[PDB]
Amino acid sequence: APLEPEYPGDNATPEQMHQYAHQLRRYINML
């Protein structure tokens, strides 16, 4: 069930943040 991911820490490194936000836009766009 690939839907709404989970934010990486209150403010994770640009790397982890990019991964999460990436999947977010990827999913929303996937559907």
Image (spheres, rainbow, N blue to C red):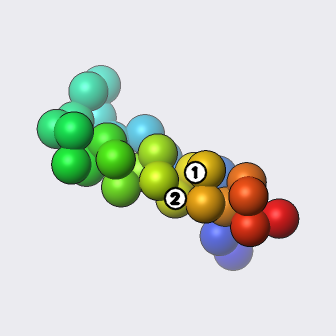
- In this view, the residue in front, 16 or 1, is 16
Q: Is residue 16 visible?
A: yes
Type of residue at label 1? Leu
Q: Residue at x 61, y 50 (%)?
A: 25
Q: Residue at x 73, y 58 (%)?
A: 29
- Residue 27 locus on image (x, y percent): 67, 61
Count every numbered label the image shows and give the total: 2
Q: Residue at x 46, y 45 (%)?
A: 21
- In this view, the residue in front, 9 or 19, is 19
In which quadrant is the N terminus drawn? Answer: bottom right
Measured Cα–Cα span from mark 1 to mark 2: 4 Å
- Residue 12 locus on image (x, y percent): 22, 36
Which residue in the protein does label 1 denote?
Answer: 24
Which residue in the protein does label 2 denote?
Answer: 23
Q: Which mark is residue 5?
A: none
Type of residue at label 2? Gln
